[PDB]
Image (tube, coloured by chain):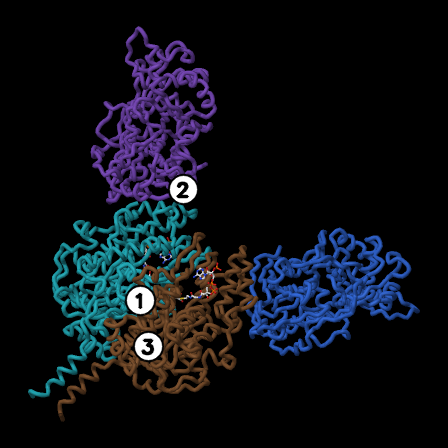
Chain colours: A brown, B cyan, C purple, D blue
Amino acid sequence: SAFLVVFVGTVYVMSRPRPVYLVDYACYKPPASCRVPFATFMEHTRLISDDDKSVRFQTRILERSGLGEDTCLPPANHYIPPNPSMEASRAEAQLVIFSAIDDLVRRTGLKPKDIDILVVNCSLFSPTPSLSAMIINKYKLRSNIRSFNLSGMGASAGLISIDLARDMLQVHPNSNALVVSTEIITPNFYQGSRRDMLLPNCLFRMGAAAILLSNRRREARRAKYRLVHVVRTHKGADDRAYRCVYEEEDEQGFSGISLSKELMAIAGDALKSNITTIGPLVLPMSEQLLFFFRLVGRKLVNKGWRPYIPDFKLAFEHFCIHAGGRAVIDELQKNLQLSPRHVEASRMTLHRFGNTSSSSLWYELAYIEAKGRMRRGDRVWQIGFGSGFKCNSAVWKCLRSIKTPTNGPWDDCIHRYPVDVPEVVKL
Amino acid sequence: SAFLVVFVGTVYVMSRPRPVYLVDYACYKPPASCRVPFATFMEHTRLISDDDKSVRFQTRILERSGLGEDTCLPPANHYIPPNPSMEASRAEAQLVIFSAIDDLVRRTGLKPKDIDILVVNCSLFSPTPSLSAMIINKYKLRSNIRSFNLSGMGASAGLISIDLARDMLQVHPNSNALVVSTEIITPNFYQGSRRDMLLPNCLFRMGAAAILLSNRRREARRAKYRLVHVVRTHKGADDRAYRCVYEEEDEQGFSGISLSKELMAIAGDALKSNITTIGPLVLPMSEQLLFFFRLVGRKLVNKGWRPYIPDFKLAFEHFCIHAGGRAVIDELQKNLQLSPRHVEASRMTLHRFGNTSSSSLWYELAYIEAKGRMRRGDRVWQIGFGSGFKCNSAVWKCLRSIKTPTNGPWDDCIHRYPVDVPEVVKL
Amino acid sequence: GAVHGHRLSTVVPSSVTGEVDYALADADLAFKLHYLRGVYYYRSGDGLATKVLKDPMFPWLDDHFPVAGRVRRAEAEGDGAPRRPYIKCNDCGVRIVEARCDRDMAEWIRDAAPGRIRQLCYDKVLGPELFFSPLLYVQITNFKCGGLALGFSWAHLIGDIPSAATCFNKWAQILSGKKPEATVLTPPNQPLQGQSPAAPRSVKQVGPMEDLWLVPAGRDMACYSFHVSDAVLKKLHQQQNGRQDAAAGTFELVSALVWQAVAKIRGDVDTVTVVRADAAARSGKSLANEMKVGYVESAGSSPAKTDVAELAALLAKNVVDETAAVAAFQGDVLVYGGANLTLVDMEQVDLYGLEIKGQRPVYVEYGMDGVGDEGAVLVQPDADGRGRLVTVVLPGDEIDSLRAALGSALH
Amino acid sequence: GAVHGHRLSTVVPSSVTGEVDYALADADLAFKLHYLRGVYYYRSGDGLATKVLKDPMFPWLDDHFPVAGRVRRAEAEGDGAPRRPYIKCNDCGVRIVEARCDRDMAEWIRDAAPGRIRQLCYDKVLGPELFFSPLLYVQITNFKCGGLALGFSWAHLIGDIPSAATCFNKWAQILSGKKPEATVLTPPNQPLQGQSPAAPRSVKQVGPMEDLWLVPAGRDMACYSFHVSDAVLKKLHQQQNGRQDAAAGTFELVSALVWQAVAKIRGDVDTVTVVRADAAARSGKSLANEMKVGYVESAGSSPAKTDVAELAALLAKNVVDETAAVAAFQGDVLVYGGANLTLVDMEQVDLYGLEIKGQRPVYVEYGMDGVGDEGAVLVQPDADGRGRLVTVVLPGDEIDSLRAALGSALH
Ligand SMILES: CC(C)(COP(=O)(O)OP(=O)(O)OC[C@H]1O[C@@H](n2cnc3c(N)ncnc32)[C@H](O)[C@@H]1OP(=O)(O)O)[C@@H](O)C(=O)NCCC(=O)NCCSC(=O)CC(=O)O
Ligand SMILES: CC(C)(COP(=O)(O)OP(=O)(O)OC[C@H]1O[C@@H](n2cnc3c(N)ncnc32)[C@H](O)[C@@H]1OP(=O)(O)O)[C@@H](O)C(=O)NCCC(=O)NCCSC(=O)CC(=O)O
């Protein structure tokens, strides 16, 4: 063939999807003027409450939580009792978000007229106008910007916004996307005494991340990662998984997030429904033969062999399990059969920054970058789980080797990390 | 030539966008047990209020509001004083939404396992798990559904949801997209006494719309409309238009929507900024020539001429301006030079249903379909303005002539509409 | 064991009435100062949740839309002396007061203590905000034994007592699934002239109030509602020996016994008032104040110690009827207990026809409000349909001694 | 014109300390029952919002991390008869109390009424939750003038009074933009062995206290801060004509004046305590109790008959210092006001070195909490550096008698 390859050469390049490049991202580093230690949190709890059945419960929760002393709460939970105002929660949203976009536009050389798509997510706090309209008002973005504000979707909506900005960058060529993933802790606080609602008091901390995605080929040599796959999984059709992370009000009228005791069994079963989709996508077919050389000799001889799970350590170099709690990283390690060096970004992110809900994956990625472990061609797996039990996952591929002076949230304190973490905090 | 013309039929055919078809929609008609007359509202206000200045204000607001006697409030504002609980807010979200999707799946034969994209928008009420997860839990949708929950984006977020479902149907072929556009009035009631925050009490009423879009070409003989354009215009960069519809807390701590007195001057300038984008897209070139020939003679002949923007009455046959208030449709009519029959769906929708925030455009479309005026090939213009002053606009093209028994929200009352709405109702 | 947790709500007509002005008759504006309090007790109140009880109130107010209207006045730009009220039929609605009482209902029915129809009815009045005051209040009290008490606070302006009871039974028939009888509001009421400046002796000209439609008595009333049994009814038929008489043995004898008990304690109760809820005097209208007001006097010896057969034959024969001059008068007139002790004939009124689903009431008592300081006597039917229930509205200083005087005869 | 609107908040160290245990000295545990109440008045608090004042407290507590810790108890190695406490350096923080007062500050400074130091310092104590009680409270009171009052409630366990004052001045130096000097915690405190089973006659051995480090008085205590001027100081120097004196002419004359003034009120206060803040006894440490506590007897005539010159002569030389036997005693003791009257020498202490931006304080007064019912005399410096200020913490029975007994000499 000599002339009928241009028809193949134009049916392949117009059907190939546009690549979505992660140019750079900036994570909000909260200051040491907002850190809440163990003893400060426990004395703040002991002053406002009267019963020593809730304080002794929160002591065990916070000492088995896997957090540290540098975890930061907003400047309203430093008061006894706290002040969950609307202006105090909106000014915190102008602190964690605007300091993450200012850090991003000074390291990328980004213009505010260059941003075409703006996808902001924050679970509980959703003011009128949006946080996206707040960003548009502050940075003077264009009138034809395509802004979206996904609210109420929990701690897995960071990858929902990443998949949304991916699907918007296929329709619109030569565009930049701005993804902001935050969680405002000032209206998240629980003023009551129900024990299932006091676990979000001892877990969630300050944090945000501004993410710059693009599909231009000019920003393919400056870019850090290429988005390979985003795999979503919604276990909300089950009634046990839908009412797992449920926002209720107690019998005294205080709103809050009520976690279930069966959450870790549901978070494990939301991952294995996500593993069965992302498995054929990322595993090499050198050993994707577990379903054709091993399964065909089962239902005629013996159903059930002793377990040899698909080794995901052959498909990925880095793992970014969402830092929900200590016991959830402990279980998803044993489901994936991970080494303790693989779950090190998640553990040290929960230790240093706490359960920053929608943006823990970016603090984990900045940990893997700032340790000098992000080499060229390394594949990254970000597993993120939240409310409604959406368990979304993203596979990034590193384009260029990151140099260890990173200018991220970790560079002030990563000479001490990884810290050895005993499972209790003695008091 | 006769052999190398396949390069024309491979570059042009694979670069055209996928057509998005509005298959059907279903607006929630509230029952007559939840209706609030004028006297019931002005007595429920007068029993709680100690201030006799606020009732003299809300009398004037509700009597010049353009609303009617069939406007429905949720079953928590029927109490004296109201009880805006969260269980009562979820009971309304399970009522206005699950009765508009049940109306849609019985008139289209839609299966819950066919829905691939789910875009729900509600401005103020955004629980955890979100309303999209509520729809997924009730109807038992698939685990790999792409669900989005856009909250905080005001009353113009219906067309943001339509634009999002349109852009999601370009990437995913052979897909159905469910769009739910509602507003929960139960947490939106202002329990205070500030006069700028007492206008959303006298305007916002119950209503919801569930919309089924699809890019399947098999559903081109069943569908009612084809989406032509969606034009978005975000006026949030102006500091006056950003704080025009603003959610605050007053001096007593009550949260509410504070409407400004500068709203019609902003909504008119957010519309004519949207007109300059949708103008070259839909206007016929037989009278688009004033931007090609007549603007040549501005610095050539005269500066100071006759007021004449091009006629949108030649472009579209139907208009669906968002039924915000009486003075807003009065101001967006003279900015477009519309006949009283052109602003008739908006006026009768505001009279019958009130200011349903995001679903007013679908109630107006159901009004035009109920009168039998929706013919084949007719073009519809749906204008929606909201908070942050996003002012979105969409153009649909009717595919088949709608037969006048519609089974919508209007069929119990369409024989008496249009009603001669007085300027001030008789007191 | 007081009633607590009052939650206020409204029910409207399900269909828009429009700009309709319901004209009130001349007999409606004479009874405007009085208010009816009726309580309907039920043994089992399960399955009657307060959406089940409230959803038939929306089709029931479609037929009875003046009950959901509000009182306004018609302006007169001549002299400012007349301003006739009407019912502007806006769909403002009927108050629904959800309440709960943690006492036993059967122990409270047999309490015989002064004051259970005030705690079980919402004690409101077409009050100082006249233009924004409801004409009907329905209180739904749930007891801790499972009992249910429906307390109706009915304004005597919009309807009579049989009109009120038929209006409630037409809601019970919609709740039971039955088809109610059609309501006739069709011939509109017109005012009448005739120039009567002299009030009858059956009523008391109170002062020309303007926006509070209530006369305070100074001495607080109390509805003591005792029971007249079947054995003491036919025992009252043992004093008419040797004579034939047209005295109805279940109204004239009972009200004559209560008149004897009141006149034994007061000095001279010479003139009384009989306000009959007759049926042959009714038209077809569903909301009309068609009572039969008239005064009866002794005209001779005092009724303090004569026997009740003489007072019964005196009450059934010597009534001078004045129901037309009460309506033809121009001022506020205060019929119920204003000039004289009223004796009301609510005995042919279908009180126990408030069958909710299949549940006939256990006990139905009717009180009043706005009674002047002479007293009101309300002779009601019984649950079995043979005895009488007598609610007596009195200033409180006498019910301690009416129980001492009536108990010698009632055993 | 009272203080209201208290808002509580904490400031932690900016750097994590870790699992450090600050060992207390044998002198720190002898002063654990007393507390310090120091108020610093400022004329103009412009630009000094309660973020500008709170932000330098995060670098200030990195150097002074035992002040941000809590007090715990270690367990014995054999039988559990002793339990020596220590400051566990968890970064729990320092309380900040943002209050306001609508009274104007210049009127309240010159008012001479008792109870001013109690309202501007947050009166708390290492109290009923001993493991969860702060060692330092800072109250910021905004006045009607815009004047600022910093009220420092300092637990006397963690440091002395010059240690408290330099610890506050090192915060004001960070606030003013300056650089504070070195905070020395480098030699750790250790217990001693001296075999001391007998308490000195300068303290009062109170009973066993377990989880409340405050001895109650029972009477109404009152701290009365009167100012002793320069002209009355030179009138005190005319009573050693021809007599050689070694008394410091600004402390022993003034404390002798207050001693004979309260000796004319109480019966027989024969001996007194002098708590000297001696500059030579201080070591290099920044949080340590290097006081000089010792009694002094009359040893002759009564202190109510004699004059202040011979009282100062016996007050300078006849001090039997017991500051080692105070720290060496086992049981809990009461220094300030326990056994005898205490005459503190807080006069070379840099009180007015709290220049927060460029502003010298207008008035600085120090009170004490936990003083027993004998009294405490706090001889402070004034703003000019020549006159003195005396805060007398006595019961309220003899405060108004002291203002009359001192007025004959103070003019
Ligand atoms: C496992 C831990 C309880 C700590 O381990 P422990 O050893 O203390 O557990 P344990 O068995 O000994 O007992 C713990 C005590 O706390 C109680 N307890 C434990 N979990 C509870 C829960 N969900 N609700 C109410 N009570 C609970 C137990 O009854 C018990 O009380 P008793 O002593 O009486 O027996 C905690 O670390 C944990 O919950 N980790 C999971 C974190 C998590 O749930 N993250 C959700 C974020 S998802 C998200 O981010 C999505 C979103 O928010 O939208
Ligand atoms: C224009 C109207 C006031 C009615 O016309 P009138 O003839 O009565 O106006 P008027 O000139 O006579 O004066 C009316 C009285 O109300 C006061 N008044 C008017 N607008 C006010 C406002 N926004 N805030 C506070 N006060 C206001 C005026 O000061 C005046 O007070 P005085 O008596 O002292 O003179 C009302 O219909 C109106 O405001 N329509 C606009 C509705 C609107 O804004 N919709 C936005 C939906 S946006 C949305 O849906 C997005 C989202 O929710 O997120």
The Cα–Cα distance between marks 3 and 1, rounded to whole angstroms, is: 22 Å
Which residue is label 2 attached to? C6
Return the chain for callout 2: C
- The numbered mark at residue A310 is 3
Q: In which quarter of the image is ligand 1?
A: bottom left
Q: Residues within 10 Å of mark 1 (few under 14, many from 20)?
A: many
Judge if badges 3 and 2 mark residues of a common chain: no
Q: How crowded is mark 2: few (under 14 residues within 10 Å), some or many (20 or more)?
A: some
User: Which quadrant holds residue C60?
Assistant: top left
* Residue D15: percent from left, percent from top: 56, 75
Q: In this view, does B75 lie above or below B177?
A: above
Picture residue at 31% right of the left edge, 50% below the top: B63
The Cα–Cα distance between marks 3 and 2, rounded to whole angstroms, is: 64 Å
Dot 3 lies on which element? loop
What's the amino acid at mark 1?
His
- A187 left or right, relative to D290: left
Quarter of the figure that contains the C terminus of chain D = bottom right
User: Which quadrant holds residue A286?
Assistant: bottom left
Q: Can residue B167 be seen in this view?
A: no
Q: Residue furthest right?
A: D242
Picture residue at 15% right of the left edge, 63% below the top: B224
Dot 1 lies on which element? loop
Which residue is label 1 attached to? A234
The residue nearer to you, when weighing D230 against C279, is: C279
* Residue D398: percent from left, percent from top: 77, 52
Q: Disc 3 or 1, which lies upstream in sequence?
A: 1
What's the amino acid at mark 2?
His
User: Which quadrant holds residue A265?
Assistant: bottom left
Q: Which residue lies furthest to the left in this view?
A: B2
The residue nearer to you, when weighing D186 against D94, is: D186
